[PDB]
Image (cartoon, rainbow, N blue to C red; front, side, top):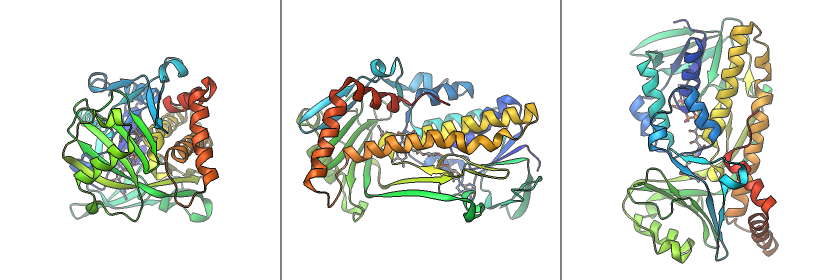
Length: 391
Ligand SMILES: Cc1cc2nc3c(=O)[nH]c(=O)nc-3n(C[C@H](O)[C@H](O)[C@H](O)COP(=O)(O)OP(=O)(O)OC[C@H]3O[C@@H](n4cnc5c(N)ncnc54)[C@H](O)[C@@H]3O)c2cc1C
Ligand SMILES: Cc1cc(C(=O)O)ccc1O
């Protein structure tokens, strides 16, 4: 097989890059280890920045999102008996966020890719990269018993955190920045109407809680839990009871509960690798970095990475200077770290940390009081929440 850009992974990163390159005229093929049904089996929600929204329109996959998508002009933070709404639209200057799940985005992208007949190879196992600093890089994999080879000019590592792409770079070339938080999120997806038309973050002494949406008949809730916890010790019953205890009464009153469609515990991690590339290999999305989901930034960061790689690959294949591709890591990392900072801040002020002292609690409380009580403070949250202007 011959292509111009070999893409590893058919997640939202790889698919979006694939479709963007398609419109541009750049040949590309995607290799996915799992099956389409499995990738779509991944039930992850989604809050979208306008940057990602507009990027889906440019890729031509905006029709269904324009229909099923839900716009939020604001978001709520609850703490210390208070409920404070952040007017995102007003504070950021017209900008908003979009409720549209990653599962839907991934579906939409697949449909556009199948519809246009672009190349995608699922069940591609033992994926291995070759000659990365060489001039004829190539990929090798096995499906249906046969061993194939995909020749290429460039390789896009969009194979997520546990992908082979990052592990294909010599470790001596990479520096890893990592923070593991002492808690996880116990999440529950239910076929119930959301308690609020905007999302609600809650800092409660018992722990963090989050009320979120998917459709308008499907809700997504989280409560922070210790990593000592196992999902089997948490009935739907126990979940709703804890969630209600961590919410304002006037919210818990209005809360429609129900059976769990999905119930899982997710650990919170920060992760960044520098640089994000090696020769003809470019990492994007979870392959390069992880954020705690408190900021809802991982998928949006994946988008910005892909947007940068797409536009550099354009100026490369067109203007014959595949040298601007050296600027990939520096450009992405500037935005990645700003996302890591906000996601870290959000996590730091909304969660309860073990073995913290009285001073830390008061500082956390004062952080919320100041930033939610100041027009400037509110603006710093808002502009980060909707997404800072692209680079
Ligand atoms: C609970 C939770 C809530 C979140 N909420 C938000 C939110 O509200 N807003 C937001 O912007 N982000 C959110 N995120 C972040 C988002 O889910 C991820 O950042 C996003 O999935 C990253 O996409 P990706 O394509 O880079 O990686 P992935 O989605 O993991 O895709 C990687 C693909 O590559 C495949 N693959 C792996 N290894 C190989 C291999 N060797 N060979 C071939 N293929 C391979 C995988 O099967 C997979 O299909 C949330 C995350 C979690 C866990
Ligand atoms: C607001 C938000 C929502 C989700 C979700 O919809 O699951 C995850 C993380 C978030 O910060």
